[PDB]
Image (cartoon, rainbow, N blue to C red):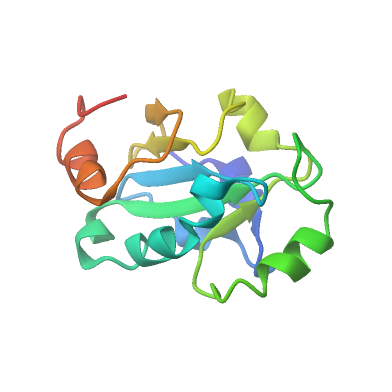
Length: 144
């Protein structure tokens, strides 16, 4: 109903990741890493999806884990990600992978849909495509 913790999270733009979410629409959390080809090369893709008019029905944002798994350390990842030409890319920082570990995300990329109520909806261990996302949201039982 009101995940205070989810809002406590911060983005790479030193802003509240909560503002990127909506308690009236389902959000989509995608975990990635600078050491991921299928992710780094998919940066732009996600940057557009979160802006896709069709995605307006379901919020879409990513999440990074600085100092976890094999990601850069805090401070650096930000200065490095700020040069990817993606100033409009929603990325929630996780000092130590708090969210990832909480959702059991060891494989990247990854996804996680959260109903408007703020409850879990689905969790995928990979990187879906355009149309894939459309159908994934259009139906509650569309892929897991």
